Image (cartoon, rainbow, N blue to C red; front, top):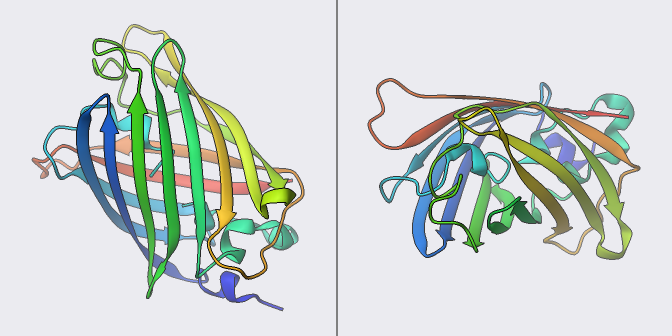
Length: 226
């Protein structure tokens, strides 16, 4: 049988992303739009900084900017927490510790508003070096592939994960961003709590040659595996 959650993702779904951020008192907002195709694990999104110049590097926000679009192959259907929580949705929280620098704390609600899948985020960053790799914009505009290990969090009726993102620094070195994550359903309904598994990610960042606002174009693929 097909679940309500699964059914909401059988075709291409429009996405809206909204973020209000404050990093060391540098306040900013970002809007994003695009589409997700969960059958292929495929996200196509464009983000705009609506407040002017983004005060942090775009790559540092990629993980923050909708895992309900992951491709869960048929044999893993009973392990797809993210879709099972829909349409009421889930809260996705992270702390992201930038090694030798500050940290982001993010809280997002991911849910449907009509036919649009919305990721609404608040981000708070503190303890950054005003001249470091983040506030000093020393990170390359690119992105590495990663596997993320997902575990059930039974107590919380959700999932958790921790994983390392390594951002390439302009001098050939790497800026580690250690991610700690917890997701919990918004509604009171049942969800699917998964066996341990992983998600394989690839992300490509580009620019729209006709766009004059500070922005990022993201093509991201995410597939579940045992």
